[PDB]
Image 1 (cartoon, chains in turn green, yellow):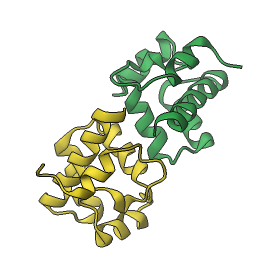
Image 2: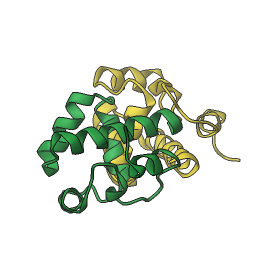
Image 3: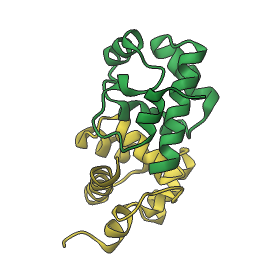
Image 4: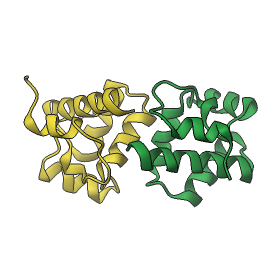
Length: 88
Length: 89
């Protein structure tokens, strides 16, 4: 299943949406991503793409970068994968 | 229209799984060097462009350092990704 946050994100181009629009990225994770330069959702998309959409490596990178737990990183990965299938 | 037809073709549609050589400025020589470094599809180079927050200087220098792109090649590749993002991201 998916959250409404996921469905809202995968429904449209992301433009300049902030990193907190990504499913799984709440205020805590969002703060830590911004601190490390990932202030917009597209920058995280960038990392997803540099990693060739690899689920294991992206979710691990997210954990190491902002401390995402497994549910959060699952949610974030899934919303980026579905967005790419629709728009990339 | 001062852009190449190859630019226009790239920016006209989602890139899907297009190879890196579909990008403006990326001929066969640059494309091979990019592929050897793991940048085999255009979307991987898009990824680097986005990780660099679409900064022209950073991206064009990364391209130079990674495949030896000259100024014109790196400008064309940057401009093609910038316009693609304006259309589809």
